[PDB]
Length: 442
Ligand code: NI
Image (tube, rainbow, N blue to C red):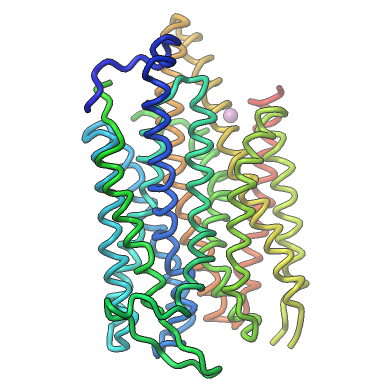
């Protein structure tokens, strides 16, 4: 039922009923969020296979389809974070998971109809973006179920396994598309040059039964708990760039890596390999957080950004001047980018929760605030900041595939976009060096 008496900080309460309830909510939240990341990056897999079905959209148009869900995603993250305390975690989780069936079902029918206008795919693309907003509400919700000591571990597991949703989708979708399942629901195949049949509808339809099962499980298994001037702070905008360069890079490369590989090395079936990128990136986010706890987020973030810049530079030497070579180098460097982008995602996030909380602490104390008020306002501000940072960092998921699409459109080469990425990474190691010299000497 709806919980009125929730005392997670009380050890006796936690041992008695708190831990068991919070364990159940967390472990229904994780699959629900994982599925959100599946639906969010759907077009990273589908847009690769649209020409194979009969669509004649330009390369720039295809990239745009992978880019757009990060727009609505970013925009809706701040509103989504406000929804949980209003409607409760259980109800909003079920609602925000369930509505993802609409673009999943729609896209399945849409890909079988080569008369479907590009405009309709734009709508579906944006609709998939709703899935990208679930992160803000899912994470906000889980924080209330855990004591401040265990939130770090609880939020890390929910977000970590959540981000795994990209890789599992980029693994499963290419596999079920070759399968003749869902025929009873009208799954029609398209004959490919190699003789095999392509069932593109399966790529989105495969999630519908799982979206439904955990929509049901959310309504029956989760609970509701009865229990900003941050924009002005210059540090908020400073940190947002860093999370933009890391999480934005992870989610941006996830959106457009397959599409790019198709434009650089068209022979390689990238879809049987691409998932590994977002896979290690999602694992490195957890690694990045763990390292940051032991050594300090800033130190981890700084070294990571130097690494992002190096591999950003090395990526130029892998590209073909269309002929020729080398894919194996190209993929290796991109794995390194995924890993560092993920690593930096976790490190930056830990860093923001530390730096912003510390400066908030020192501020209210400087105003003559009590220790009690200092701690709680530091909690409000950091929770408010991270939510806003997370929304801004999401826009990188648009920028990178949009930059690849534009660079190729006017030059025929992605190096223009990559050069922009390199400068951004070099700017970031400068930024991160600055905060290491003023705000973080620990
Ligand atoms: Ni400063």
